[PDB]
Amino acid sequence: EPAFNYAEALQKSMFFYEAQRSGKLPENNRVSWRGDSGLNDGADVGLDLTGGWYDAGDHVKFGFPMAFTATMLAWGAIESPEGYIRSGQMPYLKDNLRWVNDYFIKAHPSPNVLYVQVGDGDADHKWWGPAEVMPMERPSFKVDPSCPGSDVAAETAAAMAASSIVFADDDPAYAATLVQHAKQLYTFADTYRGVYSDCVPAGAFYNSWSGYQDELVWGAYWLYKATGDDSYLAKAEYEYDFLSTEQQTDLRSYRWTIAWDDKSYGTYVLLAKETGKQKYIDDANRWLDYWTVGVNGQRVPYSPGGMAVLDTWGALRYAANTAFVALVYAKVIDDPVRKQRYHDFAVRQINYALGDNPRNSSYVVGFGNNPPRNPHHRTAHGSWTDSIASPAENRHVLYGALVGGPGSPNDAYTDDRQDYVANEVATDYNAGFSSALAMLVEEYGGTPLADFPPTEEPDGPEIFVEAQINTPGTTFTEIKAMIRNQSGWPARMLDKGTFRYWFTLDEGVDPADITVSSAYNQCATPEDVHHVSGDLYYVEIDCTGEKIFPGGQSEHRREVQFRIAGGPGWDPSNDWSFQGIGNELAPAPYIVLYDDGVPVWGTAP
Ligand SMILES: OC[C@H]1O[C@@H](O[C@H]2[C@H](O)[C@@H](O)[C@H](O[C@H]3[C@H](O)[C@@H](O)[C@H](O[C@H]4[C@H](O)[C@@H](O)[C@@H](O)O[C@@H]4CO)O[C@@H]3CO)O[C@@H]2CO)[C@H](O)[C@@H](O)[C@@H]1O
Ligand SMILES: OC[C@H]1O[C@@H](O[C@H]2[C@H](O)[C@@H](O)[C@H](O)O[C@@H]2CO)[C@H](O)[C@@H](O)[C@@H]1O
Ligand SMILES: [Ca+2]
Ligand SMILES: [Ca+2]
Image (cartoon, rainbow, N blue to C red; front, side, top):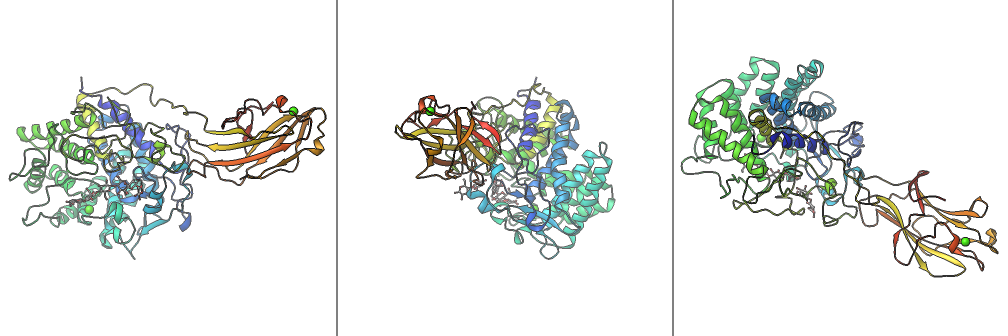
C-alpha cells in the first residue's frame, strides 16, 4: 500500500484547477462557492476573452504560466494515462485541459495575434475580495508582428499541441483544431522574434528571464509529437545548440529546473528520450545529478528533513517539477544506479509535500494531516471588507492546492495568509506536481474518495438586514437598519434591493398623518406607506441602484435610518417587523429584504 494516497491527492488537484476557473461556469460546476466572473473580459478590444484560469491567488490571467501549466498537465497525461484512469480522474483532466484550450482559441483571433493577458497586475493586486465581484477594469493585452512574444506564443503552441494528443482519440475534430492553431503560433513565434515582457506589462510578475530560445526547442518538439512531422524534430535539435550555457563553461545550464520560464531542462530529457543521443543524456544527467548527488562538489540545497530547496518562492513547486521529470527520465535511462537515484529522489520529494516531513504535516490544502488552512488566495478567503486580515480563517477549503512551503533549508513554515512567498498557490504550482502524482498512482496505486467534493454550507446569513432602535420614542419608531452582503457561496452583487417594515395601524392613528423621515439614509426615503389589508401596512425602503457587494467596508453595506411618526396612539408592540429589535444592532428576521422583488432574507406576515 502507498505511503500516502496519491489517487486522492490527484483527485483534489483537479478540483483545485476547477476552482481557478474564470468566465461563465457550466451547470455541472463542482465548486459551490465559485460563480461567474470576468464576464466582460475582452470587451475593451471587442473580443470575447472570457474563460481560462486565474493565475494564482490573484485574478490577472497571465498567458505565459497558464500555457506552461497546460503543457505540463498534458505531458503527465501522455506519460501516465493509466494513472489518470485508475484514480478515475482522466475525465476531469480532459475537462480542465479543454477549459484552458478553449480560451487559447478565443485568444488567437488570427494566426499572428495572441492575447496573452487580461487584467492589470497592480490594480488587481490592490483589491482583496472574491472574483465574482471584482470592481476594477480589466485591460486586454496582446502580441502581434508589431511587438512579438516568441516565448508565450511558442508555449501556447506547445500547450495546444501536447493536448491534441490527449484528445486525439476522444475528439479527433478538437485535436485537429488545436494542432492547426499550434502550427500558426509556432510559425508566428519563429518568424517574429522577441521577449513578450517587452510588449506587455507582465515583467514584474512573469518576466521572461531566460528568453525564448528554450521555448523554440520546447515548442518544436511538441509540434513534432502532435504532427509526426520530422522537420519539427529537426528544428528542435538545431535550436537546442543555442541554449544557455553556464557562467564560464560551455556546459548547458544545470543549476535550476524546469518552470514556467525555463524549459531547457525539459528538453534535455525529452530529446534524450526521443533520440537517445549521448549529447542529451549528458545534459540531463548533469542536471539531475546536481539535484541528487551533486556535480563538481556543488549540489542543490537540502534541508535536514530531506527537501530540496531551490528558491524562496514556491519551493515545493520547483522540487515537484523536478520530481516529475526525474520519474520520466528514470524510465528511459538504462543505468540501474542512476535509475534508482532519480526515481527515489522523486518519490521522496513528493512524499515530503504530502506529509513525510519534520512537521509531519501536508502542504496540500485540504489533504492529509495538519494541512494549510489559510493560503494566500482571494476567493478562497472570502473577505467582504477588502482586508486580508478579516476574517481570520479562509471561508473556503481550496482542496488540492499545493502551497509554496519552506523557502529555506530548515523545514520551517507558518500557515500565514499574508505570506505570498511561501503560502500562495498557483496553476503552475500543481502542474509538475499533478504529473508526478499520476506517475505514482500508476506505480503505487491508491483510491479516490467516492463522495467528493463535500458541499460547504455558508458560515451564517450571507445577505441580511440588521436593525436596532436608534432613538426611543412614544409617538414614533425610529429604526437604524443596516443592509449587509457578506456572501461567499458564491459572492454576489445585490444591486436591486428593497426591504419592507410591516406595522399594524393603531386605534387613533390616521394613516394620512403617518410620516416617514430620516436624518441619514444611503438609500431612498419614502413619502407614503402601503396598505396591505385590514390594519396591516408596510414601509418600503428602495436601495435599487446601490451596488452592495462583499468587496469593501462601505461597499458591502448600506445604512438606513428611518423614523415612522404616527402621533399619539402609535403603538409598536403589535407591529410585525418590530418583534426582536433591541438596542444593539442585530439581524432582524422580520424585515424582509428583496433582490429584484424576490425575498432573500426575513419572513413576511
Ligand atoms: O537566475 C536563476 C534562474 O531564474 C529563473 O527565473 C526565475 C526568477 O529568477 C524568479 O524571480 C521567478 O520567481 C517568480 C516565481 O517563479 C513565480 O511563481 C511568482 O509568481 C507570482 C506572480 O509574480 C504574482 O503576480 C502572482 O500571480 O502570484 C504568483 C505566485 O506567487 O513570481 C515570482 C517572481 O516573478 O521565477 C523564475 C522561474 O523559476 C530562470 O528561468 C532561470 O533560467 C535562471 O537560471
Ligand atoms: O506580486 C506579489 C504578490 O502581491 C500580492 O498583492 C499584494 C500587493 O502586491 C501589495 O501592493 C499590497 O499591498 O498587498 C497585496 C496583498 O498581499 C498578490 O496577492 C500576490 O498574488 C502576488 O504574488
Ligand atoms: Ca524561456
Ligand atoms: Ca402598531
